[PDB]
Image (cartoon, rainbow, N blue to C red):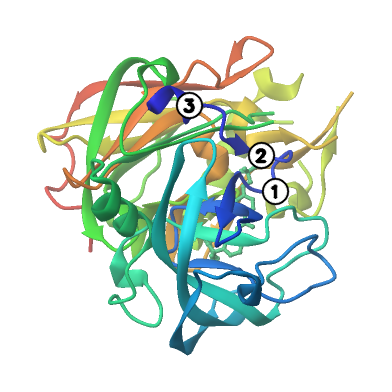
Amino acid sequence: NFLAMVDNLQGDSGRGYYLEMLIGTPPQKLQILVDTGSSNFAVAGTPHSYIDTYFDTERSSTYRSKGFDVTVKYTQGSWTGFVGEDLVTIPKGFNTSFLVNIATIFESENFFLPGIKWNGILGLAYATLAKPSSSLETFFDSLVTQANIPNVFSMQMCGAGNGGSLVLGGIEPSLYKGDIWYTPIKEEWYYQIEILKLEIGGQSLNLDCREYNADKAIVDSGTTLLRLPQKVFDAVVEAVARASLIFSDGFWTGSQLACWTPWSYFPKISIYLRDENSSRSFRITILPQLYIQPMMYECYRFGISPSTNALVIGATVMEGFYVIFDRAQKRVGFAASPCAEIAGAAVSEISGPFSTEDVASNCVP
Ligand SMILES: CN1C(=O)C[C@@](C)(c2cccc(NC(=O)c3ccc(OCC(F)(F)F)cn3)c2)N=C1N
């Protein structure tokens, strides 16, 4: 029933796309961040002054404790929760109960932030990232097993410049347009893909392709901006600045906004990805509309930021496409998305193929 998995995500103007879930018996309703960058299902298990609601295990007759807690740390934020299992329903999609592992948070720091509307997280990446270990089966793996659905999910995020769709168990034709292009997953932990080349206003950066996979290049719906390793971030900033000619130093680091559209003053940025046939590639392109972001005449943020360790294709880039996480065939797909528009104007482009003769056979160090 793919057509009832349409418009099941709310985007609350850029603070994460979240899905509504009924958890336990009788059902408690949560709002859950959809995150392709982690692998735990974790929800608030006690009151917190920044959330409206939490999951109370004592009010569920089908909840079973698993007899250990788990501590998770991120670069920013951390939490400890009890591990247990309970029944889950997704009203917009899966109105049949499946039993999943769940972490109920009773201690945290800089995790529930003021104004945020989600009170848990749905981690959709591979078991290898699961905490405390890969043997804690992930939500999607439980769904695949119990529902006999294919091992594929996909995502349309429609909030460029208000929500979108998570399709569990497949692909929805009305959500994309034209051809799907697939790039292999290189490692099944994150959705790690192989980036071959960055191009600014039609000119490629002068950097070894291994810089782009410096550690890892990943597709992560739980990250806001396009994130780039420092070296790559600094080269991109120079290439953008020179190709537009308008800037205070603080615009590039996110410490100032620029107030004025400006979009015609900035260049396209293209990411080249290896195609499932290794001898070609395809590119995804974002227009200034996605990375020069109106915040409220208007005032604008640079939608790219530095990372210590990863190139992260985050939610702002994903708003430019229909994205297919084809676990079964070990690939990620990208297609043009009808809803990737600001007042009818396109925000993004996708094209291919291109030869990969000018580039190393393996760009992943
Ligand atoms: C990066 N990352 C982490 O650092 C750990 C973890 C669990 C995490 C933890 C806490 C919050 C978040 N993410 C978010 O709050 C968030 C907020 C807005 C987001 O999208 C904004 C927009 F949709 F692009 F506009 C995406 N994620 C992610 N997931 C991640 N993917």
Q: Amino acid at mark 2?
A: Gly
> SS class of the residue under badge 2?
loop
Instruction: Find disc 2 in the rendering and name its residue.
Output: 11
> SS class of the residue under badge 1?
loop
State if disc 2 and disc 1 touch (CB < 8 Å). yes
Which part of the image, by quadrant, shows the N terminus? Answer: top left
Which part of the image, by quadrant, shows the C terminus? Answer: bottom left
Taking depth in this image into account, of 142 and 172 the one nearest to the observer is 142
Question: Does 59 sit above or below residue 348?
Answer: below
Instruction: Find disc 3 in the rendering and name its residue.
Output: 4
| Residue 213, visible in the rendered structure | no
**How far from the left and from the top, in percent, is residue 244?**
64, 28
> SS class of the residue under badge 3?
helix
| Residue 250, visible in the rendered structure | yes
Disc 3 and disc 1: Cα gap in Å? 24 Å
**Residue at x 39% of width, y 61% of height:** 99
For ligand 1, which image quadrant applies?
Answer: bottom right
Instruction: Find disc 1 in the rendering and name its residue.
Output: 15
Q: Residues within 10 Å of mark 3 (few under 14, many from 20)?
A: few
